[PDB]
Image: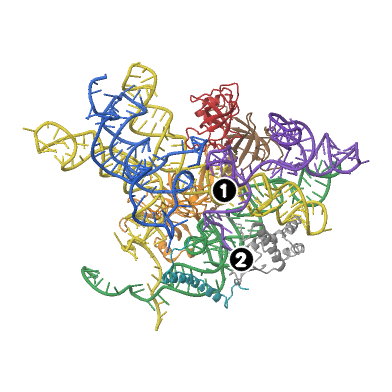
Chain colours: A cyan, B red, C brown, D orange, F green, G purple, H blue, I yellow
Amino acid sequence: AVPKKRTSIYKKRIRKNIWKKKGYWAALKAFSLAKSLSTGNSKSFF
Amino acid sequence: MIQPQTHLNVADNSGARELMCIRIIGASNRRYARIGDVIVAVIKEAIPNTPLERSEVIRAVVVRTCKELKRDNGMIIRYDDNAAVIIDQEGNPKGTRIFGAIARELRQKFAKIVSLAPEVL
Amino acid sequence: QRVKLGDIMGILNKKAVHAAEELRPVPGIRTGDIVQIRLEVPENKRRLSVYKGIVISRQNAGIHTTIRIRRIIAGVGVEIVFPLYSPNIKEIKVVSHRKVRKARLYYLRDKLPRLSTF
Amino acid sequence: VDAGIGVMGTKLGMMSFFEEDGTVVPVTVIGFKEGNIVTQVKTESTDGYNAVQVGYERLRDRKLTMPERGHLNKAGVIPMRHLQEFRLVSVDDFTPSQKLLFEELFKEGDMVDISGTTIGKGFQGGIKRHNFKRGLMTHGSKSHRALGSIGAGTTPGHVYKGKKMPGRMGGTKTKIRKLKIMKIDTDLRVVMIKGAVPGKPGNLLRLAPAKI
Amino acid sequence: MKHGRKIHRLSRPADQRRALLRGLTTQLLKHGRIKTTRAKASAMRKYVDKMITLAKEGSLHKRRQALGFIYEKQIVHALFAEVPERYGDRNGGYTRIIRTLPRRGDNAPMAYIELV
RNA sequence: AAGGUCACGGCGAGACGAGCCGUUUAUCAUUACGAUAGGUGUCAAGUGGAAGUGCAGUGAUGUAUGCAGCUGAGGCAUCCUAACAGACCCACAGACUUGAAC
RNA sequence: GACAACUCUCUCUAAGGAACUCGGCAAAAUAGCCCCGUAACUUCGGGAGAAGGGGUGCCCCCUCACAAAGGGGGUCGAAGU
RNA sequence: UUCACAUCGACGGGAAGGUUUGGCACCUCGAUGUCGGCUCUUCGCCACCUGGGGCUGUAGUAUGUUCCAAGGGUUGGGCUG
RNA sequence: CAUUGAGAGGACCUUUCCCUAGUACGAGAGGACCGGGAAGGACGCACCUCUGGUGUACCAGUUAUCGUGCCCACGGUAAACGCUGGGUAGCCAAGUGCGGAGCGGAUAACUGCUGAAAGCAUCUAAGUAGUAAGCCCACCCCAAGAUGAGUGCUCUCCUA
């Protein structure tokens, strides 16, 4: 359970950039919702 | 479903009352003894005017069971107790009058149990 | 002249019950009745077995609309299942009716058997 | 290599056929949404093997993409969803142009094999995937239902591959074998088959003769 | 595995879920338009369609089952005097599940229930 | 561009990703597709006789209305509600070299 | 939100009943009030609530210490502390 | 019964294995947690069974011993940690 | 989309009973090899038609109490069902189906067929035949990240 050693700058920038790329994937969805929130007949967002 | 530590009542007047059955013969499953499987009984208590006493290993036949009995005709037969017949390896028992009803498939291997039975359903 | 949908459970089951009713008529067995079952078993030559008893349930799933029946044979407690649409039965006879306030008489197994002898 | 062309059909529940002898047999009911039209045959000349390619489930054209519907209209047939071939020995006489093959070929052949997607059970443990035993439920025990030991001691230094771990159990296709056919219906488009097919009512089901 | 278990259970135990259903469909029948989460929205949709069509046939038995389900006394008797005059000929589909922005603090998918 | 992804309504699929099925003048007619989910209407099915009234009884209770009443995770029908509004990725003959016939 | 494995706190479990185990550990079972009845042994104080068995809900009537309580009867439920 | 070698083989001799008890003290004590049980492997053959065969003081059944073969199986319990 | 399959997994297990036949063999007593059939056991892959377990979707009986003004009738609570009685769809087995096939290939031990080195011989030195639950293939599934990245069908590359 206890880690034997530490990680490099290598593997950490890989994992942190996979985390922040996983943050990248959930804003073109927000760009699509922000673009559909604009002028148009949409039956949502009262 | 007859485990190797069950108590079976007697279905004859051979001289016992119930039995702790031990480790069935034939079907090598031995944790599920259905009908017609002989069991290596031991006598838990008996009738004390008969040459069948306490602590006596004997062979018997499971003839009634609380577990179901799938038949090809569509019927399913089940009893409310467990019963055995104190048997010998040459067919017939050493007790004549059979108590309680039995089924009829065990006629294909144990015909003397059926012929001495009061009801064959 | 109509093509059929994926509702073939009800029409295979319905025409199966209608065919088995065309073969032999069967009055309905409600829960709590006291009925007779006349069974056809080969090689016995008596060809009419006696099954008196009390219907405990009716697990009706179309062609397995069945009878959980119970009669105290002189030893103890015999509990037989009968498919009502099988070709092995001959006729049913609703002898009596207990008029019981229950759909499932599973209590009656392990009761005092003077109230269970058909 | 299969011993002949088969069909595919959908499961529509289970019931019990009453044989006139008196027996009660549990049968699965097979329907047929659309005829199993031979769409594309692949012979020894233009392909390395020989197989007959049939399909199933005629649909709307919006449900089907341009390469799919272009492939199906290359044969001049209806646009259909499912599509599978049977590899067959080089004695075949099958035209890919709309052979709406009728289901009479299985009744005299009272042995058939079936393949299908079994129902998935998700990420299940080792107690049900590989039929393990659980530990003691009491007597101060703590390894209830757990996986137990995994490998040997120092000398391996690892665990053997293919070791029985928990994982996703169902979802792959299976074939159960030599299943004896029963009463077909030439108007209800329904075949009784005594057994238990893989999956709930609704899924695709390969129905092809035996390979014994 | 959840094959065919079509009850929609929330993040709450069973009796607390029943009280959430009864209270939120009660105040849904009080205000008409309401802000829920989407799980709570569909969970309102089934039960409030059951309560519109329950007092559609305004007998005493339907009114007593309907009064037994809803908390407030004076809202059941304002219901069967309103639903045959309004929701006759609709024949199902009494609500609308207009969704909105997620909630600040949870990113909870947040919905909004009408009566139409 | 073909084809995907998000979103959308979900699943007999599923820890999350996956996968699968829909994503509407959601047929018109002579005969297999354009009902995805919820509701509704019915049919299987479970418990099993509901409330109210009348009758019998001093009353507990039983009885008729009434296989009624609820349940409807399942089947079929029905566009009543939600499948609206969108967005994004991938484009523009697929390097270089030999042989064959045209 | 979802309703994976698996841990934990609980509920039930066909057939059997300790075969599990170091060991009935843990769970299950008994359980309240009245009536009957209660053994070996003993320091004659006890064991003893030994053990074991029956009634128990609700409506009638009468006897009523005229408050507790009793008997007889009916009524339902599969099951009445 | 005759008969060293169907089967045992005395007095002795030659090997293989590293599964017992030992010998050395070569890694490890700024820590390599012993014995049994549960769960779960996998491997060896010096084969208990299953498959094929030789010999038999093998009439047949059942064997005794031995060759090839490790794919698969090798029970439930009373005692005791 | 459709598959070939290099490679890898799983499965290739086993017992009584009956015919042959109370036949060969044996003074009797006993009792075959070989070839078939049938019922099992474990293991595995599935399924819920039947039988059930659970099923806090459900409905039904009842205790204590608080609300719905009160009687009736309901709702809440008695952990994550108050305690029980049953149950549809799921899940499961104890239940239900199915599997373990091959006069297919080569062999290990062995039996051989011709047959020489020593005009006799010998299963072998040339060639070659029967044959093991063992090896491989066939059997069920995954499978071209098999970078050796396969094969077949079909769609689309437009304007300046």
Q: Amino acid at mark 2?
A: Arg
> In the visual, does B16 lie left or right of D87?
right
Q: Amino acid at mark 1?
A: Ile
The residue closer to the viewer here, H15 or C105, is H15
Total tally of numbered discs in the picture: 2
Whether D34 is drawn above or below F64: the answer is below
Mark in front: 2 vs 1: 2
* Residue at point 31%, 57% (across, down): D48
* Mark 2 neighbour density, 10 Å: few (under 14) some (14–19) many (20 or more): some
Image spot of residue I48 (x, y percent): 55, 48
Which numbered tag is attached to residue D30?
A: none
Residue pointed to by mark 1: C11
Instruction: Determine the chain carrying the residue at label 2.
Output: E
Q: Quadrant of residue B68?
A: top right
The residue closer to the viewer here, F86 or H28, is H28
Image spot of residue F17 (x, y percent): 49, 64
Contact between labelled residues 1 and 2, with CB atoms less than 8 Å apart: no
Q: Quadrant of residue D36?
A: bottom left
Which numbered tag is attached to residue E38?
A: 2
Instruction: State whether residue C41 appears in this view.
Output: no
Same chain for the residues under marks 2 and 1 in the image: no
The residue closer to the viewer here, B38 or F69, is B38
> In the visual, does F40 lie left or right of B108?
right
Helix, strand or loop under label 2 = helix
Instruction: Determine the chain carrying the residue at label 1.
Output: C
Whether I153 is drawn above or below I19: the answer is below
Helix, strand or loop under label 1 = helix
